Structures are given as C-alpha cells and as structure tokens.
Image (tube, coloured by chain):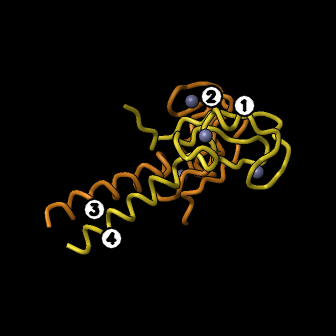
Chain colours: A yellow, B orange
Amino acid sequence: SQQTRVLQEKLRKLKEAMLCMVCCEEEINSTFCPCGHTVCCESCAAQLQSCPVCRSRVEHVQHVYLPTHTSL
Amino acid sequence: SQQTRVLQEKLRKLKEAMLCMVCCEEEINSTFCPCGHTVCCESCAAQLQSCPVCRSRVEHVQHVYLPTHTS
Ligand SMILES: [Zn+2]
Ligand SMILES: [Zn+2]
Ligand SMILES: [Zn+2]
Ligand SMILES: [Zn+2]
C-alpha cells in the first residue's frame, strides 16, 4: 500500500541518521571529546582535528558501544 | 498489507533500542567513560558507580549529541 512506501522511507531515514556524516558508509560509533558530537565512524573521526559539527578542537575520540549497533 | 506490519515492527524495535536501559522512558544521551557503554539517559547515568553492562568503574559520564535525538 502507500503506507508501506511511507514506512520504508521512515526506516531509511532513521538508518541514514545512524551512518557517519563524513563517509556515509559506516555506522556512527565515535564521540568527539569534550564537545560530545557523536556523528562519525572511527576512521573518519581519527582524521579530524576539529569537530565537523561545532569546530571545537578534538582532545580525543571516545568509542561508543550503542544498543542499535548492527553487523554482517 | 502484511509487509506494512513487518516495517512497523522494525521501526518500533529500532526506536526502543534508543531508550535508556534503566528507566525505559528517556532517550540514551550519556556514555560511561572509559568503557564506552552508551545505554542510559543523563539522570540514570548520574549515580551509577560501575557500568550496568560490563561492571567497569565509571570514571566520568560524557554527554553525547546524536543525530537521532528527537525528544
Ligand atoms: Zn566515516
Ligand atoms: Zn562538536
Ligand atoms: Zn533513564
Ligand atoms: Zn561498560
């Protein structure tokens, strides 16, 4: 039905919100500290000296273990 | 259709996985450091001495701003 299409779009958008904002390919699993923006995978987060959301300096990256995490 | 019910279930499960494991009412927005378990809201994370998942000592709690935040 048309509701199947609406729900597929909602699911796609929620899943996209959990993917890295830089590479768009891997799940978010890293927080920039101390600002707290949690928007990147570990690979993109390691390459940024400044937060890509607020531009605060990244003192270090904290790995986050989230219940929504998925794998092959 | 039955396909619509399957998608509704998937959406509901993903949304429930974003809620605090202690109060089940507020969104997760806090990390226990250094272990990294990110399973609680700010209130529930505040008085835990050890991680509720791995039992590691909680040295401090880091607030997290996630793109899925809606509350
Ligand atoms: Zn990435
Ligand atoms: Zn930031
Ligand atoms: Zn809570
Ligand atoms: Zn832990």
Q: Residues within 10 Å of mark 4 (few under 14, many from 20)?
A: few
User: Going from the N terminus, do you reach mark 3 or mark 2 first?
Assistant: 3
Provide the residue designation for mark 2. B35
Task: Write the residue at 21% across / 57% down.
Answer: B6
The residue at label 3 has a CB less than 8 Å from ligand 3? no
Which quadrant of the rendered structure holds the C terminus of chain A?
Answer: top left
Q: Residues within 10 Å of mark 2 (few under 14, many from 20)?
A: many
How much space separates mark 3 and mark 2, taking CA atoms? 33 Å
Q: Which residue is mark 3?
A: B8
Residue matched to label 1: B59
The answer to whether the residues at label 2 and label 1 have Cβ atoms under 8 Å apart is: no
Chain of the residue displaying label 2: B
Spatial CA span between label 4 and label 2: 38 Å
A69 on left or right of A53: left
Give the CA separation, mark 3 to mark 4: 10 Å
Q: Say if B69 sits above or below A27 in the image.
A: below
What residue is disc 4 on? A6
Q: How far from the left and from the top, in percent, is residue B53?
A: 50, 31
The residue drawn where x is 69% and y is 37% is A45
Q: In this rendering, which labeled residue sits more in front, label 1 or label 3?
A: 3
Q: Which element is circle 4 on? A: helix
Q: Chain of mark 1?
A: B
Residue A71: image x %, image y %?
Answer: 40, 33
> Which amino acid lies under the numbered mark 1 shown in the image of this protein?
Glu
Q: Is residue B56 above or below residue B4?
A: above
Pick the front one: B1 or B17: B1
Is the CB–ligand 4 distance for label 2 below 8 Å?
A: yes
- Number of marks drawn: 4
- Residue that extends furthest to the left in the rendered view of this protein: B2
Q: Amino acid at mark 2?
A: Cys
Q: Are marks 1 and 3 on the same chain?
A: yes
